[PDB]
Length: 304
DNA sequence: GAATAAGGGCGC
DNA sequence: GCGCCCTTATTC
Ligand SMILES: [Mg+2]
Image (cartoon, rainbow, N blue to C red; front, side, top):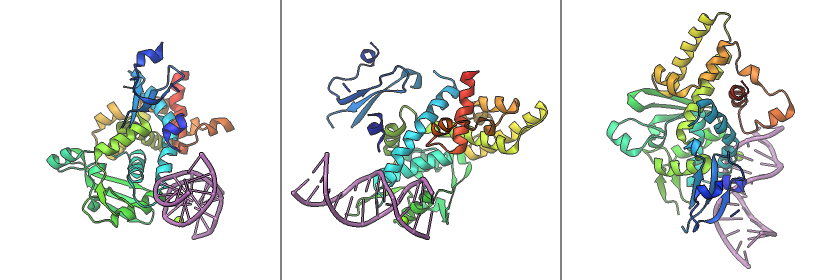
């Protein structure tokens, strides 16, 4: 199903000032929800958001983002089930790539001037498929050599279909007359507004950077001395920095939630935050095993 | 909206 | 790798 289908009628509500001409307006029955209202204009979906999501700590924003990911999965799966390569299916594939591989979206005007690439400006020459392994190799932002890879069956099968279309561009849609065009950043960003707004494409990189860091630390394992632990944190930041195509300083400062490092320094990793009851597991549906554990780790900061 | 057809993701 | 069952398109 779609997101608005799932979320599904017209003092707080008054302060939102939802335009009266909007049709089939829905409103949150709750002061906390990041999406406070949604409806349709004469033509398209319009939204009003919680102001704290348009000042929160990283751990707060990410816990809430993890709450939106199961809905994202339902919406993107629905779009992926379509036949051929219609716009929403190609955008769902691109959204999966943002999620699982932590791409920047990019833009045409930026790419044209800088001769560097992001997801929406990738060329066919930037990717290869070997069975279920999709590998990307491209010049990313600031000229950094970027490498990314995925293992998902659906991505691999559909990447092959995209590569069957005439080049040079990778992300194109075909209308089932056969008319062909690119998916540009503006169109993808509108799709994201629908399926995750008020969260944005950047939230995939902060969530994904934090997740990769947490996985790395769990896999490396805890250290007996805090000094030795801090060395592991240095290695972790540099690994995630390479994945994200950023400096270690920017990665530590803006991408990895420090809560993950706090827990590591106290000898706790993702393994320690696995669900302990059947409902605790069920509430993590639509998250990967490691994503679920990350959500629970971030939730421990609220608990204290 | 319902009945119909058939492509195709993802649980198994 | 199979195949249930969710998807869009078509017709009423
Ligand atoms: Mg098949």
